[PDB]
Image (tube, rainbow, N blue to C red):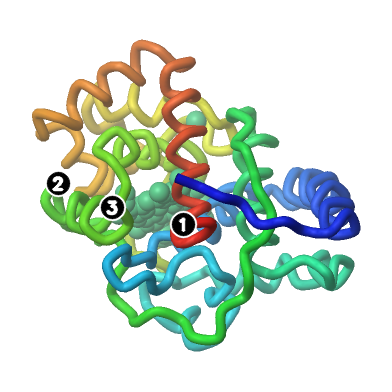
Amino acid sequence: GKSYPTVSADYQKAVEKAKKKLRGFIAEKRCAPLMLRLAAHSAGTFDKGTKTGGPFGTIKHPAELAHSANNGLDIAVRLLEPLKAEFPILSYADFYQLAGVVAVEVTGGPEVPFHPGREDKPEPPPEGRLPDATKGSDHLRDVFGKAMGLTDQDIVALSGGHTIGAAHKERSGFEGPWTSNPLIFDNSYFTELLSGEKEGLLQLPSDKALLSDPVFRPLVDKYAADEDAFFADYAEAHQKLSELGFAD
Ligand code: HEM
Ligand code: NA
């Protein structure tokens, strides 16, 4: 239901060049997971009823970074500032979604379609809209479904974003990678979810909720069995997420 806005040729040129520089920067710095977190976690403040929040660069604001659920994201914002300064024409909104798209690509993930044109919004959304790692399927549906307007399929596919990276005890309080290959985007997050708790690896209560739900569970099984089907559903979900409140 998207109608993407027109941007100038010079805008499109900056996106292409930013995309390449982001690949190099993110690969070298080994920060694909934190970048994916910044893009996705920050898009997830969207509330469809009121058309507030969402992927509009408000996460740059010290006020939104201060939200306890955003512990560590100030690192991400700080890391990107010098590169962003090379592309003054790009909104921060687009730049952070581009960094998320690139984070998935450089780690071996699918090519998520990207459309420019998000505008930087003045006011952060209220604290507390983010998914709670201690809660379950009802909470996931409240947040991704009722607020964001995403599907049950989207929920499971997006949870697979945890196939890269780790929790940190000084950030959320949780600790460790979800997989044995935390810089590799693949279906191992679902493989690990099915095989039970392996020593050294993390499952959040939000991750575990996927196994006990009658709708979520077939999706976990499908993705564990079929990485291509994961990659397809994932690219679809991530595009939608990055586009919440944008072009409709
Ligand atoms: C489903 C609801 C979600 C919950 C409850 C959740 C919760 C969390 C928590 C608690 C952390 C750890 C923060 C830390 O201690 O460093 C984390 C990290 C992460 N999240 Fe999520 N998240 C969710 C959705 C998503 C989505 C939709 C994506 C992107 C598709 C995503 C991508 C990531 C990545 C890549 C990391 C690792 C960051 C790093 O390595 O520093 N998450 N998540
Ligand atoms: Na992995």
Q: Estimate the spatial distance between the alpha carbons at disc 1 and disc 2, rounded to whole Å.
A: 27 Å
Q: Which amino acid type corresponds to the residue marked 2 in the rendered image?
A: Ser
Total labels drawn: 3
Residue 175 seen by the camera = no
Q: Is mark 2 within 8 Å of ligand 1?
A: no
Residue 47 in which image quadrant: bottom left
Q: Estimate the spatial distance between the alpha carbons at disc 3 and disc 1, rounded to whole Å.
A: 17 Å
Q: Estimate the spatial distance between the alpha carbons at disc 3 and disc 2, rounded to whole Å.
A: 10 Å
The answer to whether residue 28 is left or right of residue 61 is right
Residue under label 2: 137
Label 1 element class? loop
Q: Quadrant of the N terminus?
A: top left
What number is the disc on residue 248? 1
Q: Earlier in the sequence, mark 3 or mark 2?
A: 2
The answer to whether residue 43 is left or right of residue 88 is left
Label 2 element class? helix
Q: Earlier in the sequence, mark 3 or mark 1?
A: 3
Q: Earlier in the sequence, mark 1 or mark 2?
A: 2
Between circles 1 and 2, the one closer to the viewer is: 1
Residue 76 in which image quadrant: bottom right
Kindly give the residue lying farthest to the top in the view shown: 225
Position of 183 relative to 26 (above/below): above
The x, y position of residue 212, in whole percent, is 10, 33
Position of 97 relative to 104 (above/below): below
Q: Residues within 10 Å of mark 2 (few under 14, many from 20)?
A: many
